[PDB]
Every structure is written in structure tokens, then in C-alpha cells.
Amino acid sequence: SYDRAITVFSPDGHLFQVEYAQEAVKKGSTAVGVRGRDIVVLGVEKKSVAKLQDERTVRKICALDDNVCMAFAGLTADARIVINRARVECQSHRLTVEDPVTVEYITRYIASLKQRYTQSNGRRPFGISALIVGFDFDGTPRLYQTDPSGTYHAWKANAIGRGAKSVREFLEKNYTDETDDLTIKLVIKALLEVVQSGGKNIELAVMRRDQSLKILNPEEIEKYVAEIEKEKEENE
Amino acid sequence: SLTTFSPSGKLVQIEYALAAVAGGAPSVGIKAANGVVLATEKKQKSILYDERSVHKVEPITKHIGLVYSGMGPDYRVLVHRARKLAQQYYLVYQEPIPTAQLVQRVASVMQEYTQSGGVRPFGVSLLICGWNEGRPYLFQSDPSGAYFAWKATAMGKNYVNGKTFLEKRYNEDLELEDAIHTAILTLKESFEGQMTEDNIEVGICNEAGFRRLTPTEVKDYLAAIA
Amino acid sequence: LLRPGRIDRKIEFPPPNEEARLDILKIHSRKMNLTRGINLRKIAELMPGASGAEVKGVCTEAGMYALVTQEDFEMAVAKVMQKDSEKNMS
Amino acid sequence: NQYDNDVTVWSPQGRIHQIEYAMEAVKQGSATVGLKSKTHAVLVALKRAQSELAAHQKKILHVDNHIGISIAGLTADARLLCNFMRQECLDSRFVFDRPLPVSRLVSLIGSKTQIPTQRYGRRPYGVGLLIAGYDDMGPHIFQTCPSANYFDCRAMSIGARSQSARTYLERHMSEFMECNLNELVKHGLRALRETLPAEQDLTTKNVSIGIVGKDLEFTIYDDDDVSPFLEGLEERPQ
Amino acid sequence: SIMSYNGGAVMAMKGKNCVAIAADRRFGIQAQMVTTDFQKIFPMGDRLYIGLAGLATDVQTVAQRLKFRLNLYELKEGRQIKPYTLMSMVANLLYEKRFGPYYTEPVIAGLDPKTFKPFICSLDLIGCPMVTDDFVVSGTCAEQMYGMCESLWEPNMDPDHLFETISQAMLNAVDRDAVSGMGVIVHIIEKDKITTRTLKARMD
Amino acid sequence: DRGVNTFSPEGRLFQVEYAIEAIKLGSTAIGIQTSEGVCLAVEKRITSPLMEPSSIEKIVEIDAHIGCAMSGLIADAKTLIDKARVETQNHWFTYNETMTVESVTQAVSNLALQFGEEDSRPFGVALLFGGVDEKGPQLFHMDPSGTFVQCDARAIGSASEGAQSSLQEVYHKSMTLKEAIKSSLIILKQVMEEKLNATNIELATVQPGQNFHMFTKEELEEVIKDI
Amino acid sequence: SAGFDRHITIFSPEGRLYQVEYAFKAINQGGLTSVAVRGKDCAVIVTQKKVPDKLLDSSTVTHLFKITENIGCVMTGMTADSRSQVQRARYEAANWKYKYGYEIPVDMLCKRIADISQVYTQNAEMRPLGCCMILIGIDEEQGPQVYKCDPAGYYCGFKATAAGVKQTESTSFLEKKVKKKFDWTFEQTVETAITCLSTVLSIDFKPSEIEVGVVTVENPKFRILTEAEIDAHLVALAE
Amino acid sequence: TGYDLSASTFSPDGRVFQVEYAMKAVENSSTAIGIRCKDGVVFGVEKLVLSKLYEEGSNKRLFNVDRHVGMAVAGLLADARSLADIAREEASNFRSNFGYNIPLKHLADRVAMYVHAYTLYSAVRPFGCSFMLGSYSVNDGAQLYMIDPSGVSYGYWGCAIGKARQAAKTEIEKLQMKEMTCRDIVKEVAKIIYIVHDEVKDKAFELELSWVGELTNGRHEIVPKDIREEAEKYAKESLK
Amino acid sequence: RYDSRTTIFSPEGRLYQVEYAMEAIGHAGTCLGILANDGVLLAAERRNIHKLLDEVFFSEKIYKLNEDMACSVAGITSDANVLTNELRLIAQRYLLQYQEPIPCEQLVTALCDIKQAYTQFGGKRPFGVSLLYIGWDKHYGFQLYQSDPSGNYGGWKATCIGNNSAAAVSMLKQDYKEGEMTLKSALALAIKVLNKTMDVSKLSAEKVEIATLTRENGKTVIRVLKQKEVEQLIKKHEEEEAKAEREK
Amino acid sequence: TNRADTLDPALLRPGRLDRKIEFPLPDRRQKRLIFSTITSKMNLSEEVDLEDYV
């Protein structure tokens, strides 16, 4: 029944600071990601261009290997540290085991590092939540998410950041069992289902499970928005 | 304590150390055209004390003088540190250390003590000077790690009043003797009425080297210099 | 009350600055039989956004010294402006 | 009461209350009774369970060929001092090639438990040791405390409601010294049957007996060489 | 020897108002050469070079270490470095490996930063400096260059005769030498300009 | 009470009692010892349809005959499972044999309550251990405080009171395997909230003649539809 | 003021710190008086003892601690700080003798002890050894010396020296006494020391309470006087 | 009442309240006295049985540090045990480094510095013990010292540690202490301990007497108190 | 309320020392850089312009760090010496390791990791210093970067220092330039910005500081220019104010 | 009063502060003249020191 710190339990059995460091994730930018059957896709919203700089350094989607892709939310500095250590870890896995790195191993590493960082004396928890998408074993698409507690948690689609309940509610109301054309159009529908969907703040990158990361061009996305508006007119 | 910033202001434990410096014994130091003059104000509490034991004006090398306005017990510590550091420079480069490099390294030491979080800062403000490569210098430091460069300055009690006299009295072009004359004038502005051959203690810095004057010539000069 | 539905506008009073301070400099130096022909721009600037009538008060401080050269108003602000003082904290 | 948080703080009455709190943490263990004759030392403890179906948490544990301890209180510190005990036993068993006298071992126990009672950063050990052993001069029954003020006795009893046991030990400590193993053990459980409330009776599965003898190695017993020990009794005087 | 593992010869010569430094071009293992364009004379600031001879490992390692410390000194102090300071720096750097010694014989040749005063010095493999007025040499061949420079040196030398004197000395002492040859590079510097010439040496 | 290095005036564990409180919020699990073998069950509490059911770990594999179940906090369980896997392999290294389950859980509770930040925190997980040693099957239950005891049929976590009560109603010593399995999932679908189907629960049964594969995979559907 | 409750060694506002100026009267809990005098080629220590018990000894109540064969001292304040400071002084004098090959001058020893007290003051989490120390010794080319070391680390040293409980009064008598320019012919020193303590405390007592430590440039060894010659000086000043 | 938490901090009037509170911790402990004669030092401790649970021969506060030095502790017992081990270690270093018996002044000064070092810092508390140190040597005579909880260590002829610190030395000092050999002093200490607190607050106590001097030829051990049985046949004659 | 140390989080969750280091930035000297190709410049405000100094340092805010990079500074002064020495040592260790100059972005991220090492741990003061970067590389040309006490770095083309410079950034947006790489245009713009934002009346040249960085033939010389060209720049800008009052 | 820092928020501003002149501790030559007053309040018959406490 006090305040500090992250070592004390509540009088009713909670940790306040894990829940409170989740709030910075809950109030961050949105990024979604789905898996198709052969091509995986994800992307972030809120490019937030301030009219006078470059943005090639502020990229929220990066990679550790040729098979795996990143995303995050929350604050960006903790993402920078975790990505820096994750590149090293993926390469150290490549040092001993001669496989391409499985996604489950690097997610167990991220969650283990995050939790042994949270257990210790006065170290501030990483207020992020990453999305770790890759397809290695027989080209099987996987995507896992994280938490400041350190719980890797495998999904099939995902929504984080601001208003993630609404965005995940749209993937709920879409998500059909029944092709990279439906997956591209599903990305178009997800980014149209964004919190703002301004049309120019959309940033998406895909991977076809054999290739590397492809950064798209905001004219192809414009025709995607045009065919979404065409289907919306065809609904009437 | 020393680990956390204020809501808006500054580092209160450094401001208090600066106040403890400002509450100290006065001093004055003047950079002239050929030399630098340092002068302190050293009053014994009783008539019992000896004036040959403790020394305010203190050399760092044969051509680098240094006075303070604060506490001797910390002064001697950072003096000894500056001694060892200057002799390490002379080990490395086999050349007498320049005063700017001294002030950099001494400022690094004082800054390292201002870092967190169990040690207190020094309650000592320095006045460093020396004659390196013809042009003499004058460098004041502070407990906060900062440093400056002066033509003439003061530190201690009534440093504001002595400085307003320095702005009026001093100029750009003088010699060492006229510098000593205006220095004993601005120290005599603020000191007690009885100023003798022992209440002051004066060292100079010619280009021929540092020189710490004796009570013989100090009593000869301040025998009603004006 | 801070609900705008109770009061619409909310308008602070930005103190006078260089332009305004200089115009009011000439103003508050108008009627006093000063030592005319004097720069008031440095006075306006020495006022760091003084609260309007402070030019009048500096005029009062100046005239008191003369009891009005530019030096009068200089010493006037000197009484006025000191504290701020006390460097050695840069 | 704002001085009553840490080990380092002396009280304004001089009684460091962390020691008192560790004593009270010892007072909430199980009841146990240890008592010796001239030739045999017997310590008897009481088991409890978490539920009906589960097994009983054991108290008498082995240490060495002639050393066995009872216990009450915490179990992590119990096993910690157990490992330290076995370690110091096999240390001297390696070096000197002799069995340890008990008194120097318990002095080492006090010196071990001294450090967490004086510096900051460790708690005093909640522990309820009743030590039985054999040096050259016969059986010894020692007890410890979280204040490391170890005692030697001839019959002690620590744990919950152990004071009626102490009254029984008062009124039979003169009688203890002469007898052989069997009635000695049944005096021990004629202390344990008063360490219990009167509306229930001591069964097989909840009691434990450990005998060390001058020629007999330390041995724990459970229900089967205790079914011989449980007969030879009458009812309580209702 | 270990000094004769990769060959090498560095000559520096003080003139009247200018200074000339020259070295060989050959790089190779004990008897097998590899290339003719191996650099042994490095720029350390303006109008001041250094020459390194001996094991090539210590040449490039000490050259990069010295460039590290040199740029740290010239960035801590805005002025440029005096040659005695550089000499003492190389002495301290070599004496830090008192028992782990580099196998090199550094030669420093440079001008005064304020005046046009020339300067030459050389060091040993543990950091023993030696300032002279005529010439210093290093490398495998010693007695050849000593005989040539003690034969050919004059006190007051125009830069042209300086160039020709160091040219003839290096050519004859290198052509008599076995493990060091295959071309000569010459740096002749002064207050006004910096000249670098390569000579037609015997490729044998 | 604030701090793991201060007792109570009475008899409070605090740094441990709040952990024993923190157990109670977790999902339930039920393991039952039978001489035929040890069975075990758990509830996943699946939240989303995107929540892939086979990725949530509750029953993991320690040895070829040693199973497990976790509780409450996830990652303290991950730490203990990792170390437990490592140490049994060390036992097989130096002894060419299988570390028995009592020795496994003593090896876990050597540091299951060893929390020290100087000279870190206590762990927040309850564990259910089942295995087949030389004495037949064994069912074992530990706690955060290291107070390890054998239990014949222990239930953990949420709703464990009625789980123990209705478990003590039906259980005795000479039960069979499948009867205990359906008696467990009856207690499960009395203590869970959602409809019992193929994806909610998972079983783990170990037999002395069926040491390998301590799991039932979608024959569990056939077991559930028999109620 | 505080306010800050002055618990650790920090700087308070305007402008002092309170830990050391609380340590300056840890001397005052000693209940003891010390006087040192330098007039001429001698130097005299005088300090009384407060022994109420007949069961208590008299040899081991000595406060005069012979630091080295030419350096003496006396201590006031609490006893443990004093004795630990004395063993530090002996250890560092022996360190001087080992490192530099000759006998330590009394100035460098006071400097080293002051520096130790300053390091104990600069870093926190240690008590600042609340005892005061007066030293004496003979040096060639400088005559005799009398020095004082503070618990703060402020050494000084001077002609007529006094520290303890009642030494505002002692320095008042020593200003009213060391103002006349007579020489100090060693019995002048002993007489002025005995009578200055006899006017500050105003007791005029037996020769068995005060301790007298002297050093002279005729025998540079430190020397503690005997009851007979103490009685001789006391009746020699008895008129 | 304001600032008495740490052992490093001072007070507004200049003393450490931790040391005072540790000093009056030993005041509640058992009464322990000591006295020397012209050829030896005699110890004596009023020791009490709890009720009936002791064994009369446990936890003896009369320790035995060196071959000729032992303690007469009173206060917290385990702290005294640790301090006795430190004293054994110090005598061990001296015997190993110089080849002869430790003088009691040097031993007492090392122990006083060790106790003072536990009074200095803020991480640790001061000791809660107060003990006696006696000795004898053929070239030194008898020496009896005394260490408080603070670390002030000096010498006595007689002392007392416990409740009746004044109430023992009221009639300790009327002993003709010089002209007696210690074999009289045995029953003297017996009568001194027997005077204080026969039955008033507690029920029963028990006497131990340690013994060093010339009669043991430099050894230190407990008396055969049952031999000559000098307490009780005089204790029953000391009630009138 | 939840103040005590730099760690741990506040209950929303924000940080305490990060914002308070920013509010320690806000009361300091004003810096800026300008959009220019074939060169880049810096502007700086002189703190403590009192008449009894020496000015013999040639640089109080600029620090020519490697050869082809300098940096301005703002904030608490003496932390920056620790930072500049360590930054020079990082870049110099890189040059030692590769014998190629440092390509400036891993330099910026190295200093950001140095600052972030004191943002995470406890309990240490975070560096309350923001500072600029000009420089040149083989991979992008002329660059500009903004270090921040959080460890975030933003590549700008027109930067921001504290409370004196929000109106400066407003003038930089409302007077945004693109295409004109001419140094004289950017210098006149900087003169205009510091004329509005600084309270120096008529812009005395002793109260300003200007350093530039151009690419010369293979050298990338850094021109910390002297005072006379500043004087004629001020006279040029006051002639442009006369052009502005041609509208009357 | 003993304090004035609890003030000058509106009293010392353009309009209010028209002739506000703080009067704190002065220089010296007061103490001497004060002696000359108060020491003359007592007798100080004809020859009794003044400066020794000035």
C-alpha cells in the first residue's frame, strides 16, 4: 500500500508498473500486421511529416535477418536498444547454429531479456511492444507480439498503439478463412481502417517469405485506396 | 541531493557552495601587459598566530601562480592533485604544461566531484595564472567546473564592490608595479583598517618566472603606497 | 468560470517591448525639461519588457539624481534594474 | 514504532525487535520434543499437512552418522543450515578423519548465524534446531535460537503450545536419566500427547522419532517402527 | 635478423634552410619481394614527415597509433605541434612497450612551425632519442649510408645540391644493399613548398 | 512491511504472502496421482480467435517421463523450466540415469525461494510436477516459498477451494485412469466459464508403460464428447 | 536554518555545514584542558587529569602520547578518536621514516593528519573523528614548534596554544600575557603554563593532577616530568 | 528525539545517541565484577538460571582467549562470542609474528580499535557488550583492563558490569586490595556477588569465578570452586 | 509525488528528468543551422558578454570535433566537456580502426547511446545537453542533426534550441527556403532570425558567433569566421531593413 | 518586519512603486556614533574606551 517500486506487490496482488508501462504502449502510434499464406505483410501509420526534414532515419520497421521483420510501439529509444541487441543475438545464433534463425527463438530471447530486465533492481521496464513476423520452417508464416511483462504470444493478425481495440475489431470483422491479392487488399482495408487514414501517412512493407523487405510507393497505395472506394461504391 | 534536477531551476548544492565561496576571505588578481599580480587578504584571528606556516599564494610550477578564496583544507587537496597532474604532463611531454591545459584538467577534476552523489563539491574558487609563450594569462574557475578568462577580477567579501572599483581604476595597459599598486588599493578598499606586512601576502608572475614576494619587499612597497 | 461559455475572450497583457518601449520612452520624456537630444532606444532596450509606466518611474529616478541627461535615466534604471545582478552562475 | 523496521537499529530500550519478531516466527512452528538419557538421546517431532489427501511435511532430517537435527520455522533457512551443517561435517570428516564433537559444530552454527544478525542486508534465520549427537562424553541435546544464543539442556521442547510439554519435562526430568530407549521414547510422546488439544489423538502418520545411540547410528522412523512405539499407552485422564 | 625480415632503409638529412628525407620502395618477405609502392614516409602535420623502418607490422601499427595521438593533441590544442613534442610522444609510445617492444626505428624530420628552422632526430627500438645536425639513418643497412653521408655532407647546402647529395647517397648505398632496393622515394620540403620525387633506381 | 528483509511483529511472510496471493489470479490446473499413472489438466483461457491455442504453454516436457504445469506469472515459470531442464541433463551426465521427481523438485526449490538483491525478488509461480520414478508414479506440488510437499491430487490457482472440495468428494486411493480423467474435466467444466470444447483444455498423462508422449491430441475431443 | 535537519555532510543555505561545527564540541564533551607554550628554545605541554577513583590507576590515564622520539602530543575530546588518531600518526611517521630515510618534521605530520581528517570529511558515511590534537617537536634551522590539528582538517601552529573546554579564557590570558616582549627562559615557560592553567581553572592543586610534557634544544628527546620535579616547579612558583 | 537513527550522524548538541543506547543495553545484563590482587586477577559473574531449563554449565560467560587471558563478558552473548573469536585471532597473529605472549595493553588497544571501527560507520551498529580483561606475567605483574561499548579502554584495580555497577563498587573499594593474595579474594568476590540481589527481583542465581595469577604459574582457568567451597559456607555467614 | 529519482516512471507514463532536462535546455544560448548545399553554417549567441573577458579561445560554443565536423552546444556547460572529449575519442577510435573518417550517423548514435546509458540506469543524472552537428561524408553530403537528452536524434534541415528560439523556428517555417544553396542568402536569413529573436539592439557583432563548413577540393575546411565580415553583414542587413522601409 | 520576500509582487511594479526605497542594514560609522549615543546614555565618566568594541 505504498508507491515505489517494481519489486513490491500490491495489497491485492498486482504489479502497478507493468500495467503502467503498458500505458505508454497503449498511447502510441498504430501498427498492424497480418499473415497471408505465402506473403506476410505489416505496416505503420502516422508518418507525421513536419514539412522540413528527411524521414529515412525514423523508420519504425526494420529487420534483424533476411527472414524476420520488426515493428514496435511505445517509446522509440527502448526499441532502438532492443533492436541493437536483437541483431547481435540473431547473429550469435547464426554463430553456433547454422540454420536461418527461427522466429520463436528470437521472440523467446526478447521476452527473456525484457523480463530479466524488469526483475532487477530499479531498471525501468522497456515500454514497447514489438511485432516479430517471419516465415522460415517450410515457409510457414508466423507473427508474435510482445509485452512489457515479457510474454511472447502468437497470433494470426494484430493491432497495437492508439485505439487498437477498434482496429483489431475491424480485423475481427474481416478475417476470412477464404492468394496475395486478398492479402494486399486486406492491408489496404486495414490501412483504410486506421485511426485517421489520411492517405499519405500510410507506410507499409511486405515480405513474400523468400524475398527481402519491400518498401512500397505511395501511388500504388493510392490506386489501392481507389479500388477500396470503388468497392465501397459497389456495396451500394 | 545531487542526482536529480529541480522542477525548473539549478543545482542548489552548487549554488550553496558558491555562496560559501562568496562568504570567504577576499582576494584580487590582475593581468597586466607583462605580468600577472595575485593578492589575498590573510587576517589572523588572534595576535598569537604565525605568518610563516600557512601560505595562500602557492606555485604550481616555476612560472604558474595560483590563489583561492574559500577553504584551505580543500584547496590543499586540489593543489596536490594539480601538482601531480602537472608533473605527469611534464613526464609525458618533457615540457612545462600550459595554463589552458591545467585549467581543463583541474576543471575535469572538480566536475568529477560535482558528479553524483555522495561527495560534496569544493567550496573553493581558484584564480589561476601563468606566463606561457610570452603572453601571460589569468583563468578563474569555480566549484561548478566552469572557467573564465579575466583581465582583472576579485573574489571573496565585497567582490562586487571591489569589482566596481576595478572597472573604474584598472585599464588595459599597465606594468607589474602599477598593477600591484592598484591591487593593494582595491584590496585596501575592503579589508580592515590595520593592513601590515603580514595581513597581505602577494606573489607575482614575471615572464622570467613565478615569483613569490617576501615580507621585506611587501613591507617596503605597502609602506603607504599612496 | 474558465468555461468559455461564461467568458468568451481571454486576453493577457503583453508588456511593451523595443518599439513600444521606445515610443513610451519619448512619451515619458516629453514634458520634463530634460537635457534634450538624448538616445532613448538604449533605455527602451534596457527595459526588458518593463510594465508600461516603468518609463515614467525611470524618469522619476533620473530627475531625482539631477535634483535630465541620459546618464540620469541610466542611473535610474540602474536603481530599477539591479537585481538582476549577481553573475558567477553562467 | 518507526525505529522498529531494521536489524541495525538499536531501540531506545535497547531491545532490537527484529530479534523478538524472529522469536515469534519460531513460536509458530510445529511442536517437537527432545530429551536424553545417560546413554541414548531421542528427539520426537510432530507432522502436519496442507490437506487431507496430501502427505505430511517432515521435520526430523538426517545430517550425519551421529548427528541429527529437529527443526521449526522456515524451511529455506532450514535446508540452508542443513547444507552448511553437512558441509562442515564432511569438511572435518575429510580433514581430521574423525567424527565431530557437537559443541564446536554448534559454535560454528552460532558464528554462522551471527553475520545475518548484525550487518544490514540479511534477515535473522527463523530456525528451530534441536541437535542430538555423540562426542566422547555421551549424548548431547542442544537447542538454538534466531538470536544465536544456543543452549545446552537435558530436555527441551520448542514450537506451538510447547509449554505444557515443558511442565511435563519439569515433572519427569529427574526420572529421565535412568531408563532405556522404549520408555524414554514413550515419555517423549507423553509430552507430545499434551502438545495437542484434547479432542483429537496422536495417530501414526503424524509423528516422527529419531534415535541416536552411543553404539547406534542416527536413524529416523516413520509409522512402521513407530507402530511398535505407539502401543504401550493408556488413554488421557479424562 | 628480425630487423632484416622485410628490409628497409630511411635517410633524413638536414640542409641549410631545408630538410630532405628519403626511403626505399621495396616490400617483401625475407627474400621474396612483392611490391614496389609500399609507403614508409607519412605526413604528420605541415612541413613535417616521419619515416619508419623495420618490421612493416610495427610500421603501420605505430603509424596509426601515432596518428591517433597526434590528432587528439592537435584537437585538444588549436596550435600545431612542435617537433620535440612529437619526439617525446614517440619516445613515450615506444617506452610503454619496454618489454613488449616494437621492431622499428622511427625517423622524424620536420621544420619549425614558427620559423624556418629544420629538425632531424631518430629513435631506437625502446625510445632512445638522438638529435643531430647532419643526417640520421635507420633500417637494415647502416654502415653504407654512414660512409656515404660522412663522405658527401656539407654544412651549408642549397636545396638542389641537397637533393643530389641524398640522391647519390641513397642510390649507391641501396644498390650495394641486398634486401632493400627496387626504387627510391624522396621528400624534399621547405617553408615555401613540398617536393616529392622518385628516382630511376636499379630494379635488380 | 515494505521489503523482503524485514519480518512482522506477528507471523507474516509479506514478500512471500503477497506472492501466494499473486498465485490466485492465474489460470487453474488439476493433476491427480493414480498408481496406473499421473494425469494432469489445465485451462488456457483463450481470449482471441487470433490467439493460437497450441502456442500457449502450460504443460511442458522436462524429461521423457517428467511433466510440468505452471501458474500465475509466465516468465518466472520460464526461468524455472529452463533451469530444471538443464539440471536433469546434468544428472544424466554424471549418473547415466534419470533424476527422480523428488530430486528434481528439491533441485528447483534450492533456489525457488532464494531471492536476494544484495549479498532477486521472490518468484510468483506455483508448479505441479508429475513423473514416474522407480517407485511408480509421483505427483508433486511446490510453492513460491519452497515449501515443497507431495500431494495426491492438487489443484492450483483460481477457484482452487471448490476444486479441492469437489475433488475430495470424488477421489480416493484406488481410482483408475480414465475415471480420474473425466472426473478432472468435470471439475474443470464446473470451474471454467466458457463452453468446454477441443481448444480450451489440454491433458497430460504419464504411464510407466507409456512414458513417452505425456499428452492427448484431439482424442481429447473424443474424451470430452463422452460426458 | 535547518530545516534540512543536517543529517549528512552537505551544504546548507547561507552557507555553512553543521556536522563539523557539531564536531567542534565533541572536544567539549571531554571535560579537559590543554595548554602549549613556545617562547624560546623550549616547548611545554600541560594538561590535568580528572581521576575521582582510588580503584583507578594513575599511569594509564596519561594523555601525553610520545609519537616518535622527538615528537610529542596531547589529546582531548573523546578517547577512542584520540587513540586511533595517535596510532595513525605513529604509523605515518614510521612510513615517513621508511620512505624518506630521515626523521619527519612536525609540519608534514600535521599536514598528513589533517589530510586524513579531510578525506574522512570529504567522503560521507564515516564519523569525522571528533578529537583535537596539539603537537610539539624540535626542528633544526627552525627551533621548536607547536602545532594544532583540527577535526575539520584545518591545521595551524603558533606560539601559545590551548584547546579543550575553557580556552577562550586561556587565549584571553595568553593575549594578556604574550604581549610583553620578555624572553622565556624555560622556567618562565613552566611558570606561565602552570599559572595560566591555575588562573583559568583557579584550583592551585597538588602536583599529582597535571601532566607536563617538555622538549628542549638541549635534549631533543620528548620528556615527561616526574612528581618530584613537578613539585619542585610548583613550589618554585609558590610565593 | 530528532535524529538518533544512524551511527554516523551527530546531534545538535554533539553526541552519538546510538552509542548511548548501546551502552545502556548492557545495563540490563547480568552483574559481572572483577578485581586484582598483588599476585593475580579474579573474575566473578552473577549468573542466573531462567527457571528450571538450564543445565548449570552451559553458555559460560567466562571465556578463555589466550593461555593467560580470558574474558568476563556481560551483555549480548553472541556478540561477545564473536568478539572473543576476534581476540583469539589477534593473540594468534601476535604469537605467530613475535614468538612470545601478548602484552595486555597492546591486545586491549587492538580490541578497542576493532570496537571503535564498529562504532564508526553507518552500515553497522556498535557492539552491545562490556567485558573484562585480566592477565599476569612474571616481568609485568597483574593487569586488569576494561572496555566499554564505545571503545574507551583503560585500567582499574576493581570494576563491576551489570545492574549493580555502583552498588558493587560501593563495597569493593573498602577492600584492602593490595595486601591480600587472591586466595582470600576468592571468597571476597563470593561475598560481593552474594550481597547483591539474593531473591528480590528474580528467584535464583549461580556463581562462577575465574582465576589467573602467580598461583596458576601464569595459567588462566576457572577455579575448582567445589574445592574449598568458599561461597556457601561463608554466604550463609554473610546474611548476618 | 512520484518524483524522487530519474527511475522509475510516472503514473501515466511519462518521465521526470527528461522533461526537466528539456526545461534545463530552455534557458541557454541559442543556436541554429541553415539549409545550404555546397556548405553549411552555424549561429550562436554569446553568453556573458561583459567587457573584462579575453575572447582568446576562438570558440566557446563551436567544437571542431574531427576534421570535417564541428558542433555547437547548449545547456549546462561543463557536462559538454565530458561529452565533447568522449565524442572526439569515439570518432578518433573509429578512424584508428578503419583509417576512414566517421560517416557521422554512427557517431550521432554513439553519443545518443552514451546519453541513454544515463537515462536508463539509476541513480545518475541524465545529460541535460542538446547540441548540433554539421558535417560532410561520402554518403549524403552536408548534414544536420539534433541530439536530445532522451537519446532521440532527428535529422533536420533547420533546427531548434530553447525558449529564445520557438519564434526562430516559426520564422524558419514561414520563411522556408529550398533550392537556394548560396551561403550569403542563408547568412542574411540567419542575421534576420537572430535580429528578431535576440534582444541585442541593432545586433552588435560581439554578441554573435558564426562558423561555417565548406567543401574545398578534398579538404572540407571549417571556417570559423572573424568579426569584420560580420560587421559588413550587419551593415548589409540594415541596408535590407532600409529596403524594407522603402514601403513608406 | 523581519521579512520582505513575501512581498514585491505588485507593490514594486510600473504604477505602484512610485517612490519605494528599501532601507536595510547600512555601512558603518553608525556603530561608532551609536556607541557615542548609548555609551553616553550611560555615564562613561571621562575616559572609557570606544573603538575596542567598535
Image (cartoon, rainbow, N blue to C red):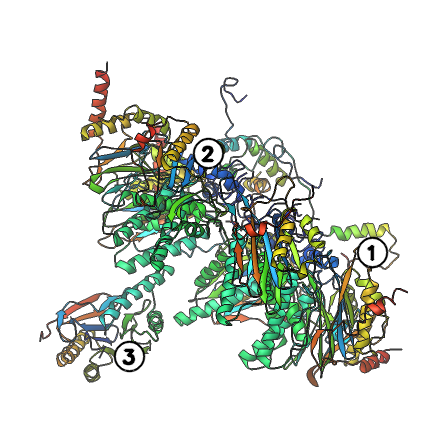
Q: Please give left or right for residue E143 compared with residue G75 in the image.
A: left
Asked whether residue B7 appears in the rendered view, the answer is no
Tell me, for residue H200, which label it has, or none: 1
Q: Please give left or right for residue F214 compared with residue E42 in the image.
A: right
Q: Nearer the viewer, residue E44 or F143?
A: F143
Q: Residues within 10 Å of mark 1 (few under 14, many from 20)?
A: few
Q: Secondary structure at mark 2?
A: helix
Q: Secondary structure at mark 1?
A: loop
Q: Nearer the viewer, residue H55 or B33?
A: H55
Are the residues at dot 2 and dot 3 in contact (C-beta closer than 8 Å)? no
- Mark 1 residue type: Val
Q: Please give left or right for residue D8 compared with residue B176 in the image.
A: right
The picture quadrant where one finds residue D174 is: bottom right
Tell me, for residue E133, which label it has, or none: 3
Q: Residues within 10 Å of mark 3 (few under 14, many from 20)?
A: few
Q: Is label 3 on the same chain as label 1?
A: no
Dot in front, 1 or 2: 2
- Mark 3 residue type: Asp
Q: Nearer the viewer, residue H69 or I19?
A: H69
- Label 3 and label 1: CA atoms lie apart by 105 Å
- Label 1 and label 2: CA atoms lie apart by 62 Å
The spot of residue E71 in percent (x, y) is 32, 61
The picture quadrant where one finds residue I64 is: bottom left
Query: Image point 59% across, 49% down: which residue?
Result: D231
Number of marks present in the image shown: 3
Mark 2 lies on residue: F167
Q: Please give left or right for residue I2 compared with residue F63 in the image.
A: right
Q: Secondary structure at mark 3?
A: loop
Q: Is residue D63 above or below residue E117?
A: above
- Mark 2 residue type: Leu
Query: Image point 20% across, 41% down: which residue?
Result: A138
